[PDB]
Length: 129
Length: 76
Length: 48
Image (cartoon, rainbow over all chains, first blue to last red; front, side, top):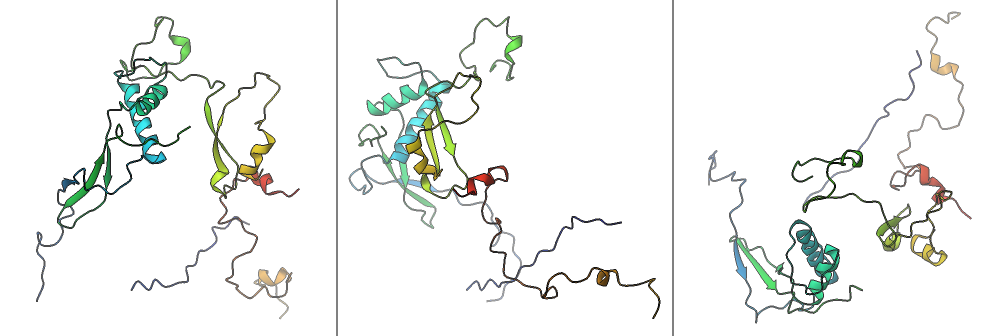
């Protein structure tokens, strides 16, 4: 009985050189749950990130708005359009998009999330064309 | 059909006669649609790009047709 | 000596190459293991 089509064999050859008494409490250790964070919004005069939307952020805004226009139907465009993509794009260009860009720069160990909330209607818009 | 949370094939929608708001329609690709165009191996950043679809209505054609100058993106 | 009943059936297959007994750990320089390209589109690797 020639079987053939063997499952081979697999070999790993390397080493991972990853460079007060105590007992078992259940509350001092463990706690897989992470502490709830508090949102610190950096004041509008202390924001040091770009006031021009990146192509990534502008694309994300347009995509989110287009999806929400696919589920909803409300908009502020005087010129009506037949596609949610067009409506969202013109909403971004006309500076009437109902979305905010939150840029997170910190995770403080005290459970503090420091963010900069940027208004796309006041921001510069990249090429996108 | 959002009202039924079900997908219907197009043969059984004679009683519909219309689509309601909230319905999702899966329509055929038309000229002007965006498509992702990719050659393996995908070595460079340009190895996947988005092209505007140009539907070729000749039933005797089965290839993907691209301008020759576009091949530099995919090393094709 | 003259028996073949439990003859080692590996020695029946005469050696084909020289160093068949040496286990070599360097990977094959022609494998497509780390190249994630489909089998049907292997023609894209062809020269011209």
